[PDB]
Image (cartoon, rainbow over all chains, first blue to last red; front, side):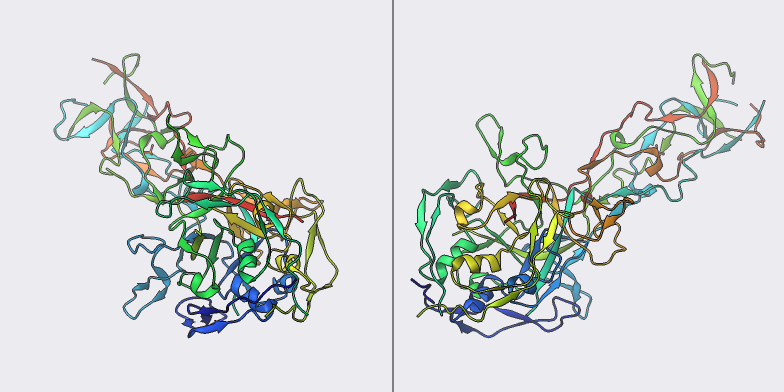
Length: 184
Length: 184
Length: 184
Ligand SMILES: O=[P-]([O-])[O-]
Ligand SMILES: [Br-]
């Protein structure tokens, strides 16, 4: 026996891209509602992998059309992890899209925000207060202690040659995959 | 010609949710084995996107039912990266689910554990041993050195006003996407 | 009415694995072009979830064949985040595959590279230059200052017992999921 088309479905929330070079908001448009009938496999494919879908393959380097048969696809998020967009606008990282600013420079509440860093290089502002393990002689106008080499009165450096210091990884355990977006 | 239904399949490993507010273990139940016949497109959809499936779209903000036609969907992992659950129980981060504790407080060996942080603020306990670049005069009961301003004998602070210091990012390069779970 | 098979598709970019134990390049082979006709649901499944596809389920612990009906599947990227492979070979982390080296030790430009760390432990090389908040007496052959306890002339330690210091998390906010690769 054969697969029934079933009742068609009202596709009311589709989108299309309006830029295929730089991908994402603001260059996305809503598609007016239309009926999808499952006339053929291509229509099923469109219901499974609508425009914007992210697809990942661990090993196949080729464009997905060559091994799926359908869709137009582009590499997506190269060098990036995916973070879930947050509907809570107070999220300071994952709600507001720095790549889609309004005329006042204000980011939209859309997916496609980017950020993060592969390493960090510590600066003095990042260091907590510390003290020497032992007492030393400290210059003090309110002090009570009266004082082969001579000495100088100066702030004592530590790590003066670390300009800059060695960076530290900021990357958690990963594996890379071929990641694609369906663009049309 | 038409797509054959094929031999049906024995779906022996399906699950359903028993809480749609707080999602995940422990509120998941096994479904007794049943036969799936591919009578219509909806049945194909259920084989591709079974309950629990994670779906991601870079650009479409809408609920996937509105552009797929099928399923019930909820945003998932907002503000989070996905980590692969580890079948090796000795993984200290990614095996045991802190959100699903037994009566003794012990986490289950299930997916849905959460953790991680967007930043770190260094504390003194995180700092390695250091020393001054030059010699200074250090108080020492076993010492041999006899000793406009006076001085005081005290531990010398560094960065005393860094209470707290500036935090450091803990986020690696990302892009946000609309991420969903099929809940029914 | 019934779903049409449609015109078949030329699958020119499929791959197969040649090792199911250790997964990935170099043990991947190209499949010569073949025609896929959508004779049955299984053929549709192969177009949606070709070999190498990554599938994620938040809650279902079982092997996907038991709840999809099709494919052979293995857990993938346990304990890992997925990063998009970079077609730009200059990416120092996410382009070149450390798990697939040539005879000179040079990594291939393929997905499957791994790296990253769950924590960092700071070392002295990572620290920026600092100085004491106040002036102290510093040994100086070019100095002009002539100098209950005695003293010693020595470099003053800080945090001498931090051998090693407390590690710091390197994990950004996450949730774990059951992640699988279709291996056949
Ligand atoms: O304050 P840090 O130089 O040990
Ligand atoms: Br990190």
